[PDB]
Length: 136
Image (tube, rainbow, N blue to C red; front, side, top):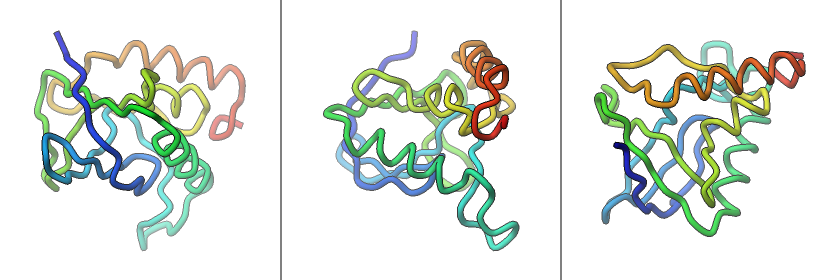
């Protein structure tokens, strides 16, 4: 069973990454199973929908009264030291909201973290069927 833990927003970084205060310290979290268009790498620069995904994530965590983190059953940090989790804002999963809104594609599973992959896949399919944002 996965369990949701409280966290406090420090700052939204990109569509896919947020810095949170988790169990007393600041930590950067990378959202599990989602790939959003980036607004940063010196390679490609700022991909289409990058700014929208960013604004999307930022709005969601910034207006939340409660942010919760949910680690999966696989590895909990990437090679860069980022926590790999599902993030919730007032009980809504940000990971899913991005996918459902056509602002992220579902990523390949990473080292056993697949609890919500099917759920995300369904949402992606729906966003695709609606030709939303990225799927437009």
